[PDB]
Length: 101
Ligand SMILES: [Cl-]
Ligand SMILES: [Cl-]
Image 1 (tube, protein in one colour):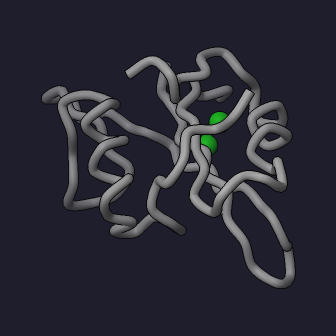
Image 2 (tube, helix red, strand yellow; image 1 turned 60 degrees about the horizontal axis):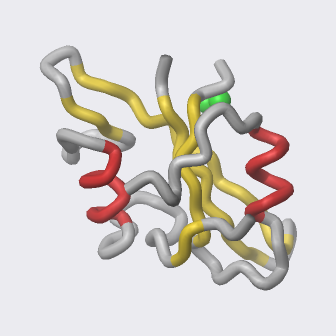
């Protein structure tokens, strides 16, 4: 899908969008790594930080496969988004809602 792909948006810009108070815990967006890789940014919550954002670097295997953890890989970013919206499996929270605006 292209809806959760925000492209060349910076890390602080994605945080300002994800920190939106109407956003359900687990709101996300995929963007290009600021530092040719991609990044999954997810909104989270805890009492110390309150509303916050987690950033995961989406890496690629040399055999062609996207990954974030060590036991799961995908053929596309859409397959990765789909898997993580069903299971958190290592992520702070599972993907629940595509980031607004
Ligand atoms: Cl980055
Ligand atoms: Cl990073």
